[PDB]
Length: 328
Ligand SMILES: N#C/C(=C\c1ccc(O)c([N+](=O)[O-])c1)C(=O)Nc1nnc(Br)s1
Image (cartoon, rainbow, N blue to C red; front, top):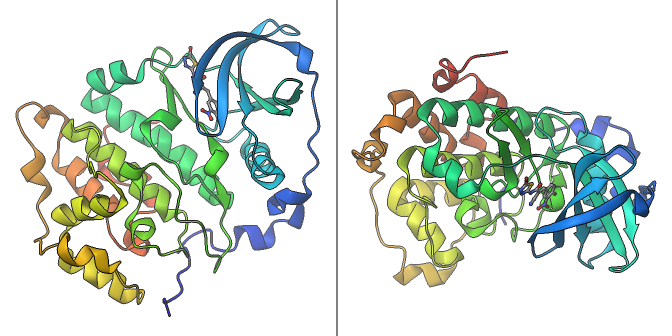
Protein backbone atom coordinates (compact mmCIF):
# COMPACT_ATOMS: atom_id res chain seq x y z
CA UNK A 1 0.00 0.00 0.00
CA UNK A 2 0.99 3.67 0.13
CA UNK A 3 3.68 4.67 2.60
CA UNK A 4 2.24 6.79 5.44
CA UNK A 5 3.22 10.41 5.84
CA UNK A 6 3.12 12.86 8.74
CA UNK A 7 3.73 16.58 8.88
CA UNK A 8 7.24 17.48 9.95
CA UNK A 9 5.85 20.31 12.09
CA UNK A 10 2.78 20.76 14.28
CA UNK A 11 2.15 17.04 14.01
CA UNK A 12 0.60 16.62 17.46
CA UNK A 13 -1.12 20.01 17.91
CA UNK A 14 -4.61 18.55 17.81
CA UNK A 15 -3.63 15.61 20.01
CA UNK A 16 -2.64 17.90 22.87
CA UNK A 17 -5.46 20.37 22.35
CA UNK A 18 -8.69 19.44 24.13
CA UNK A 19 -11.18 17.37 22.16
CA UNK A 20 -13.56 20.32 21.91
CA UNK A 21 -10.91 22.17 19.90
CA UNK A 22 -10.92 19.86 16.85
CA UNK A 23 -14.17 17.91 17.44
CA UNK A 24 -16.14 20.42 15.39
CA UNK A 25 -19.13 18.07 15.08
CA UNK A 26 -19.76 18.57 18.81
CA UNK A 27 -19.40 22.35 18.56
CA UNK A 28 -22.43 24.34 19.73
CA UNK A 29 -23.00 27.38 17.53
CA UNK A 30 -23.76 30.43 19.65
CA UNK A 31 -26.16 32.35 17.43
CA UNK A 32 -26.25 36.11 17.13
CA UNK A 33 -29.17 38.32 16.15
CA UNK A 34 -29.85 37.99 12.43
CA UNK A 35 -31.54 41.40 12.34
CA UNK A 36 -28.25 43.08 13.33
CA UNK A 37 -27.12 42.96 9.69
CA UNK A 38 -28.73 44.62 6.69
CA UNK A 39 -27.40 43.28 3.40
CA UNK A 40 -26.13 46.09 1.17
CA UNK A 41 -24.94 44.29 -1.95
CA UNK A 42 -24.03 40.82 -3.16
CA UNK A 43 -20.26 40.64 -3.44
CA UNK A 44 -20.03 37.19 -4.98
CA UNK A 45 -21.26 33.63 -5.10
CA UNK A 46 -19.21 30.49 -4.60
CA UNK A 47 -19.93 26.80 -4.74
CA UNK A 48 -20.73 26.87 -1.02
CA UNK A 49 -21.98 30.36 -0.15
CA UNK A 50 -23.12 33.74 -1.31
CA UNK A 51 -21.17 36.68 0.08
CA UNK A 52 -22.74 40.04 0.86
CA UNK A 53 -21.52 43.38 1.99
CA UNK A 54 -23.58 44.36 4.99
CA UNK A 55 -23.87 46.96 7.73
CA UNK A 56 -23.90 45.85 11.34
CA UNK A 57 -26.57 48.30 12.47
CA UNK A 58 -25.73 47.77 16.16
CA UNK A 59 -22.26 49.30 15.81
CA UNK A 60 -22.62 51.04 12.41
CA UNK A 61 -19.68 49.05 11.06
CA UNK A 62 -19.40 47.51 7.62
CA UNK A 63 -19.25 43.72 7.76
CA UNK A 64 -19.30 40.89 5.25
CA UNK A 65 -21.97 38.21 5.45
CA UNK A 66 -21.40 34.78 3.99
CA UNK A 67 -24.69 32.90 3.71
CA UNK A 68 -23.80 29.24 3.37
CA UNK A 69 -25.42 27.09 0.74
CA UNK A 70 -27.01 23.88 2.07
CA UNK A 71 -24.42 21.26 2.94
CA UNK A 72 -23.93 19.03 5.96
CA UNK A 73 -23.83 20.19 9.59
CA UNK A 74 -20.27 18.94 10.04
CA UNK A 75 -18.81 20.95 7.15
CA UNK A 76 -20.60 24.08 8.38
CA UNK A 77 -19.42 23.51 11.93
CA UNK A 78 -15.97 22.64 10.63
CA UNK A 79 -15.61 26.09 9.10
CA UNK A 80 -17.25 27.74 12.11
CA UNK A 81 -15.04 25.91 14.61
CA UNK A 82 -11.91 26.66 12.61
CA UNK A 83 -12.75 30.36 12.34
CA UNK A 84 -13.40 30.52 16.07
CA UNK A 85 -10.20 28.60 16.79
CA UNK A 86 -8.13 30.91 14.56
CA UNK A 87 -9.88 34.16 15.48
CA UNK A 88 -7.41 36.86 16.45
CA UNK A 89 -4.54 35.14 14.67
CA UNK A 90 -2.36 37.15 12.28
CA UNK A 91 -4.14 37.93 9.03
CA UNK A 92 -6.92 35.43 9.73
CA UNK A 93 -10.29 36.80 8.67
CA UNK A 94 -12.19 37.59 11.86
CA UNK A 95 -15.47 35.79 12.31
CA UNK A 96 -17.53 38.47 14.03
CA UNK A 97 -20.86 36.66 14.29
CA UNK A 98 -23.00 33.74 13.18
CA UNK A 99 -26.72 34.18 12.54
CA UNK A 100 -29.44 31.90 11.23
CA UNK A 101 -30.53 33.22 7.87
CA UNK A 102 -34.33 32.86 7.75
CA UNK A 103 -34.50 32.58 3.95
CA UNK A 104 -31.74 30.11 3.19
CA UNK A 105 -32.44 28.17 6.40
CA UNK A 106 -28.67 28.08 6.82
CA UNK A 107 -25.96 29.81 8.86
CA UNK A 108 -24.74 33.23 7.78
CA UNK A 109 -21.17 33.91 8.84
CA UNK A 110 -20.46 37.56 9.61
CA UNK A 111 -16.88 38.68 9.06
CA UNK A 112 -14.92 41.84 9.50
CA UNK A 113 -15.04 43.93 6.37
CA UNK A 114 -11.80 44.19 4.39
CA UNK A 115 -11.93 46.92 1.73
CA UNK A 116 -10.34 44.56 -0.76
CA UNK A 117 -8.53 46.00 -3.76
CA UNK A 118 -9.64 44.60 -7.12
CA UNK A 119 -7.74 41.33 -7.56
CA UNK A 120 -6.98 42.02 -11.24
CA UNK A 121 -5.71 45.49 -10.33
CA UNK A 122 -3.55 44.03 -7.56
CA UNK A 123 -1.84 41.35 -9.65
CA UNK A 124 -1.17 43.93 -12.37
CA UNK A 125 0.31 46.50 -10.00
CA UNK A 126 2.03 44.69 -7.13
CA UNK A 127 5.69 45.61 -7.02
CA UNK A 128 8.53 43.28 -6.14
CA UNK A 129 8.50 44.79 -2.66
CA UNK A 130 4.72 44.41 -2.43
CA UNK A 131 4.85 40.74 -3.44
CA UNK A 132 7.42 39.93 -0.78
CA UNK A 133 5.51 41.96 1.81
CA UNK A 134 2.22 40.25 1.09
CA UNK A 135 3.82 36.82 0.78
CA UNK A 136 5.18 37.39 4.28
CA UNK A 137 1.74 38.44 5.49
CA UNK A 138 0.22 35.28 3.99
CA UNK A 139 2.94 33.24 5.65
CA UNK A 140 2.00 34.71 9.03
CA UNK A 141 -1.55 33.48 8.50
CA UNK A 142 -0.44 30.08 7.25
CA UNK A 143 2.06 29.50 10.04
CA UNK A 144 -0.63 30.54 12.47
CA UNK A 145 -3.32 28.16 11.25
CA UNK A 146 -0.75 25.39 10.78
CA UNK A 147 0.54 25.99 14.30
CA UNK A 148 -3.10 25.75 15.37
CA UNK A 149 -3.53 22.33 13.78
CA UNK A 150 -5.38 23.54 10.71
CA UNK A 151 -4.59 23.42 7.00
CA UNK A 152 -6.39 25.89 4.77
CA UNK A 153 -6.44 23.61 1.69
CA UNK A 154 -7.70 26.36 -0.60
CA UNK A 155 -4.86 28.85 -0.80
CA UNK A 156 -5.34 30.89 -3.97
CA UNK A 157 -5.42 34.59 -4.88
CA UNK A 158 -9.20 34.82 -4.53
CA UNK A 159 -8.89 33.70 -0.90
CA UNK A 160 -6.37 36.40 -0.07
CA UNK A 161 -8.06 39.71 0.66
CA UNK A 162 -5.78 42.73 0.47
CA UNK A 163 -6.71 46.26 1.45
CA UNK A 164 -3.72 47.68 -0.37
CA UNK A 165 -4.34 51.15 1.05
CA UNK A 166 -3.72 49.90 4.60
CA UNK A 167 -1.33 47.13 3.51
CA UNK A 168 -3.73 44.78 5.28
CA UNK A 169 -4.15 41.16 4.29
CA UNK A 170 -6.66 38.54 5.32
CA UNK A 171 -6.72 34.86 4.48
CA UNK A 172 -10.39 34.03 3.93
CA UNK A 173 -12.74 31.18 2.96
CA UNK A 174 -11.88 28.56 5.51
CA UNK A 175 -14.70 26.43 4.13
CA UNK A 176 -12.23 23.81 2.89
CA UNK A 177 -9.95 24.05 5.92
CA UNK A 178 -9.42 20.95 7.99
CA UNK A 179 -7.86 19.88 11.23
CA UNK A 180 -4.58 18.08 10.69
CA UNK A 181 -4.54 14.72 12.46
CA UNK A 182 -1.42 12.60 11.88
CA UNK A 183 -2.23 9.52 9.83
CA UNK A 184 -5.60 10.83 8.70
CA UNK A 185 -6.54 10.36 5.07
CA UNK A 186 -8.14 13.48 3.60
CA UNK A 187 -10.23 14.28 0.56
CA UNK A 188 -7.94 15.06 -2.36
CA UNK A 189 -10.74 17.04 -4.04
CA UNK A 190 -9.64 20.25 -2.37
CA UNK A 191 -8.02 23.46 -3.66
CA UNK A 192 -8.62 24.98 -7.06
CA UNK A 193 -7.04 23.01 -9.90
CA UNK A 194 -4.16 25.41 -10.51
CA UNK A 195 -3.13 25.33 -6.83
CA UNK A 196 -3.56 21.61 -6.13
CA UNK A 197 -0.41 20.06 -4.75
CA UNK A 198 1.06 16.99 -6.45
CA UNK A 199 -0.16 14.99 -3.44
CA UNK A 200 -3.73 15.76 -4.52
CA UNK A 201 -3.05 15.15 -8.21
CA UNK A 202 -1.62 11.68 -7.50
CA UNK A 203 -4.41 10.86 -5.02
CA UNK A 204 -2.12 10.73 -1.96
CA UNK A 205 -4.56 11.32 0.86
CA UNK A 206 -2.26 11.50 3.89
CA UNK A 207 -1.27 15.08 3.24
CA UNK A 208 -0.80 17.90 5.69
CA UNK A 209 -0.11 21.62 6.07
CA UNK A 210 2.55 21.43 3.37
CA UNK A 211 -0.30 21.32 0.82
CA UNK A 212 -0.78 25.02 1.52
CA UNK A 213 2.87 25.72 0.80
CA UNK A 214 2.53 24.20 -2.66
CA UNK A 215 -0.51 26.40 -3.34
CA UNK A 216 1.46 29.33 -1.97
CA UNK A 217 4.30 28.56 -4.32
CA UNK A 218 1.86 28.48 -7.22
CA UNK A 219 0.69 31.95 -6.21
CA UNK A 220 4.28 33.16 -5.87
CA UNK A 221 5.20 31.74 -9.29
CA UNK A 222 2.18 33.46 -10.84
CA UNK A 223 3.13 36.78 -9.25
CA UNK A 224 6.87 36.98 -9.88
CA UNK A 225 6.60 35.51 -13.38
CA UNK A 226 3.38 37.33 -14.32
CA UNK A 227 1.71 34.14 -15.54
CA UNK A 228 -1.80 33.64 -14.13
CA UNK A 229 -2.13 30.83 -13.23
CA UNK A 230 1.41 29.48 -13.40
CA UNK A 231 0.57 25.78 -13.84
CA UNK A 232 -2.37 26.10 -16.22
CA UNK A 233 -3.73 22.59 -16.55
CA UNK A 234 -6.89 21.87 -18.48
CA UNK A 235 -7.93 19.21 -15.98
CA UNK A 236 -6.43 17.53 -12.92
CA UNK A 237 -4.40 15.16 -15.10
CA UNK A 238 -3.00 17.84 -17.39
CA UNK A 239 -2.35 19.82 -14.21
CA UNK A 240 0.19 17.23 -13.10
CA UNK A 241 1.72 17.13 -16.58
CA UNK A 242 2.10 20.92 -16.50
CA UNK A 243 3.90 20.55 -13.20
CA UNK A 244 6.08 17.72 -14.49
CA UNK A 245 7.13 19.83 -17.47
CA UNK A 246 8.73 22.18 -14.93
CA UNK A 247 9.77 20.02 -11.99
CA UNK A 248 10.63 17.07 -14.26
CA UNK A 249 9.30 13.55 -14.41
CA UNK A 250 12.26 11.91 -12.65
CA UNK A 251 11.52 13.71 -9.40
CA UNK A 252 7.82 12.98 -9.86
CA UNK A 253 8.72 9.30 -9.99
CA UNK A 254 11.01 9.72 -6.98
CA UNK A 255 8.08 11.30 -5.17
CA UNK A 256 5.48 8.67 -5.94
CA UNK A 257 8.08 5.95 -5.40
CA UNK A 258 8.92 7.29 -1.95
CA UNK A 259 5.26 7.00 -0.97
CA UNK A 260 4.60 3.83 -3.01
CA UNK A 261 2.04 5.77 -5.07
CA UNK A 262 1.10 4.67 -8.57
CA UNK A 263 0.11 7.17 -11.23
CA UNK A 264 -3.23 6.80 -12.96
CA UNK A 265 -2.35 4.65 -15.99
CA UNK A 266 -4.05 7.34 -18.08
CA UNK A 267 -0.83 9.33 -17.56
CA UNK A 268 1.02 6.72 -19.64
CA UNK A 269 0.32 8.50 -22.93
CA UNK A 270 0.15 12.11 -21.70
CA UNK A 271 2.95 12.47 -19.15
CA UNK A 272 6.11 11.99 -21.22
CA UNK A 273 9.69 12.48 -20.09
CA UNK A 274 10.72 15.91 -18.83
CA UNK A 275 13.91 17.30 -17.40
CA UNK A 276 13.64 19.50 -14.35
CA UNK A 277 13.88 23.08 -15.51
CA UNK A 278 15.76 26.01 -14.06
CA UNK A 279 13.44 28.75 -12.85
CA UNK A 280 15.40 31.34 -14.83
CA UNK A 281 13.74 30.18 -18.05
CA UNK A 282 10.50 31.79 -16.89
CA UNK A 283 12.24 35.16 -16.47
CA UNK A 284 11.71 37.69 -19.23
CA UNK A 285 11.76 41.43 -19.70
CA UNK A 286 8.18 41.84 -18.51
CA UNK A 287 8.69 40.05 -15.19
CA UNK A 288 12.39 40.44 -14.43
CA UNK A 289 11.82 43.34 -12.03
CA UNK A 290 9.87 40.87 -9.86
CA UNK A 291 12.53 38.16 -10.04
CA UNK A 292 15.62 37.88 -7.88
CA UNK A 293 17.90 34.99 -6.97
CA UNK A 294 16.14 35.01 -3.58
CA UNK A 295 12.70 34.85 -5.23
CA UNK A 296 13.74 31.93 -7.38
CA UNK A 297 15.37 30.03 -4.53
CA UNK A 298 12.35 30.61 -2.32
CA UNK A 299 9.98 29.47 -5.06
CA UNK A 300 12.23 26.49 -5.75
CA UNK A 301 11.92 25.48 -2.08
CA UNK A 302 8.12 25.76 -2.04
CA UNK A 303 7.42 23.92 -5.28
CA UNK A 304 8.65 20.44 -4.35
CA UNK A 305 6.74 17.34 -5.36
CA UNK A 306 7.50 15.87 -1.97
CA UNK A 307 5.21 17.62 0.47
CA UNK A 308 7.69 16.64 3.18
CA UNK A 309 10.45 18.60 1.42
CA UNK A 310 8.69 21.93 1.02
CA UNK A 311 9.52 24.80 3.29
CA UNK A 312 7.17 25.05 6.19
CA UNK A 313 5.51 28.41 6.63
CA UNK A 314 7.94 29.18 9.45
CA UNK A 315 10.97 28.18 7.39
CA UNK A 316 9.60 30.22 4.49
CA UNK A 317 9.51 33.30 6.73
CA UNK A 318 13.22 32.74 7.40
CA UNK A 319 14.04 32.95 3.72
CA UNK A 320 16.36 35.70 2.42
CA UNK A 321 13.57 36.63 0.02
CA UNK A 322 12.02 38.50 2.96
CA UNK A 323 15.18 40.18 4.23
CA UNK A 324 14.18 43.27 2.30
CA UNK A 325 10.69 43.35 3.81
CA UNK A 326 10.36 45.78 6.72
CA UNK A 327 9.55 43.88 9.93
CA UNK A 328 7.19 45.56 12.40
N1 LIG B 1 -15.52 37.26 -1.14
C1 LIG B 1 -15.40 37.87 -0.20
C2 LIG B 1 -15.22 38.72 1.06
C3 LIG B 1 -15.07 38.31 2.30
C4 LIG B 1 -15.05 36.86 2.77
C5 LIG B 1 -14.72 36.60 4.09
C6 LIG B 1 -14.67 35.29 4.54
C7 LIG B 1 -14.97 34.26 3.67
O1 LIG B 1 -14.92 32.95 4.15
C8 LIG B 1 -15.30 34.53 2.34
N2 LIG B 1 -15.62 33.51 1.36
O2 LIG B 1 -15.81 32.40 1.69
O3 LIG B 1 -15.67 33.87 0.00
C9 LIG B 1 -15.34 35.83 1.91
C10 LIG B 1 -15.20 40.21 0.85
O4 LIG B 1 -15.16 40.92 1.80
N3 LIG B 1 -15.19 40.66 -0.52
C11 LIG B 1 -15.14 42.06 -0.86
N4 LIG B 1 -15.09 42.52 -2.14
N5 LIG B 1 -15.02 44.00 -2.15
C12 LIG B 1 -15.02 44.48 -0.87
BR1 LIG B 1 -14.94 46.34 -0.39
S1 LIG B 1 -15.09 43.28 0.23
